Image (cartoon, helix red, strand yellow):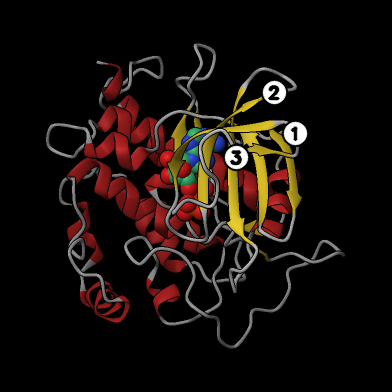
């Protein structure tokens, strides 16, 4: 039973058309904005949920206004039954787009071009003092308009954590931190209950790109967090690069050397994607796999 039924109207403005997503922490709907006449995304969480994450989501989404790869903030509110955020509506997510591919793989062209946009999104959130902590294909969606269909948008800021403080400094990490994010894309550090850093969001991007190009990860079928962590610890990460562009060794080595305290070298990773494209004769203007 959905939190909101079809045609329910939020704050005399947003009319629920259909449920477009959900699972963790609540549900997301496509709604008609009765004031502006545009289709929007309405994200809701029940007010009786023990962990309320929309307060974080709203704060991060507002802090990100003006950045590329981010939904326009439309509104938000709270009541006794539910909390909500209203934002720009996008198209299909990357997990859905990958699963729809014949072999569940994207071409290197699509993989590398998505990698550039996701890396830019990751650098954008870190630049406002926040870690995403839940980097995964379903938290990235393509635009749905002729002016936005080749733009990839970063979604879901509910599990975000501010690593900076009021004075523009980096706060000390806690001695221990509860597991946050997806099991499939979490770094080994996240599995060990270490405080997550900027490098951990880059580990999730590394695993996503391997999954995009290869179609699977070695721990794909395992659901248990601990069993997955053991596989990732034991697994020779160089074996993940068998079918990857050779400059991915540079990406892997850089992230493997980082800790919570060290600012990543985002340009080093960008250079890996750019050289991988040029060495293959891949143009930036190429159509994405799903366009064909
Ligand atoms: N602005 C949006 N436009 C289009 N689809 C969206 C939007 N926000 C979320 N979704 C869809 O619903 C799912 C949304 O959940 P999301 O905010 O990403 O995470 P969650 O349900 O894990 O808190 C996504 O994978 C995507 O398909």
Asked if residue 33 is positioned above or below residue 235 in the image, the reply reads: above
Q: Secondary structure at mark 2?
A: loop
Question: Few, some or many C-alpha atoms within 10 Å of disc 2 (few <14, some 14-19, many ≥20)?
Answer: few
Q: Position of residue 264 (x, y in %)?
A: 55, 56
Which residue is located at x 16 percent, y 45 percent? Answer: 243
Q: Position of residue 45 (x, y in %)?
A: 59, 56
Which residue is located at x 32 percent, y 55 percent? Answer: 207
- Foreground label between 2 and 3: 2
User: Closest to the observer: 281 or 70?
Assistant: 70
Which residue is located at x 57 percent, y 62 percent? Answer: 159
Farthest residue to the top: give it: 146
Do we see residue 117 in this rendering? no
Q: Position of residue 218 (x, y in %)?
A: 17, 62
User: Closest to the observer: 179 or 174?
Assistant: 179
Q: Does the CB distance between marks 2 and 3 fall below 8 Å?
A: no
**Of callouts 2 and 3, which one flags the residue occurring earlier in the amino acid sequence?**
2
Q: Position of residue 283 (x, y in %)?
A: 35, 17
Residue annotated with mark 1 = 12
Question: Few, some or many C-alpha atoms within 10 Å of disc 1 (few <14, some 14-19, many ≥20)?
Answer: few
Residue annotated with mark 2 = 34
Disc marking residue 3: none
Question: Few, some or many C-alpha atoms within 10 Å of disc 3 (few <14, some 14-19, many ≥20)?
Answer: many
Which residue is located at x 34 percent, y 16 percent? Answer: 286
């Amino acid at each position: 039973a959905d939190i909101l039924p079809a045609n329910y109207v939020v704050k005399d403005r947003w009319k629920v058309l259909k449920k477009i997503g959900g699972g963790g922490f609540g549900e997301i709907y496509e709604a008609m904005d009765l004031l502006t006449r545009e289709n929007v995304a309405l994200k809701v969480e029940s007010a009786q949920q023990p962990k309320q994450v929309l307060k974080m989501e709203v704060a991060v989404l507002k802090k990100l206004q003006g950045k590329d790869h981010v939904c326009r903030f439309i509104g938000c509110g709270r009541n006794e039954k539910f909390n909500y955020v209203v934002m720009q509506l996008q198209g299909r997510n990357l997990a859905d787009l990958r699963r729809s591919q014949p072999r569940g793989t994207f071409t290197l062209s699509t993989t590398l071009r998505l990698g550039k946009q996701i890396l830019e999104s990751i650098e954008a959130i870190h630049s406002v003092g926040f870690l995403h902590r839940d980097i995964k294909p379903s938290n990235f969606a393509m635009g749905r308009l002729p002016s936005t269909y080749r733009k990839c948008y970063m979604l879901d800021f509910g599990l975000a954590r501010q690593y900076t403080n009021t004075t523009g400094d980096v706060r000390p990490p806690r001695n221990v931190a509860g597991f946050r994010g997806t099991v499939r894309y979490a770094s080994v550090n996240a599995h060990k209950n270490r405080e997550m850093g900027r490098h951990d969001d880059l580990w999730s991007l590394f695993y996503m790109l391997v999954e995009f190009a290869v179609g699977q990860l070695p721990w794909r079928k395992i659901k248990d967090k601990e069993q997955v962590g053991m596989i990732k610890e034991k697994y020779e990460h160089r074996m993940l690069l068998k079918h990857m562009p050779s400059e991915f060794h540079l990406f892997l080595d850089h992230i493997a050397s980082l800790d919570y305290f060290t600012k990543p070298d985002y340009q080093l990773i960008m250079s890996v994607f750019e050289n991988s494209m040029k060495e293959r004769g891949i143009a930036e203007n190429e159509a994405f796999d799903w366009e064909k």
